[PDB]
Image (cartoon, rainbow over all chains, first blue to last red; front, top):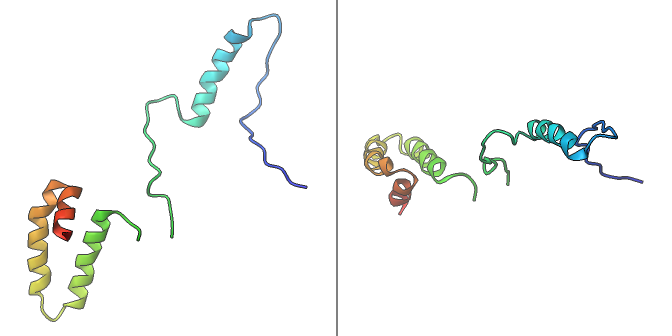
Length: 50
Length: 50
């Protein structure tokens, strides 16, 4: 057997408080993880071999 | 087959110099054309190759 997994971290979520508000702080931390928050342009053309 | 247009033309002059080391005029002459052509940018290098 074998399987592929997408880690993407693990985040605690509470109850009694609106979920949209809690998703905001995690969304910012997710953007930091992916290097998305700051303006950027992809440079991946040079990464190849023949 | 691989590599940028600039890396193609830059490397060709190095091989031209090595192959024609007995007659140094070819490398000096060929780079003279490239210096004028190469200011336009990658479009200039395409003109040199053509």
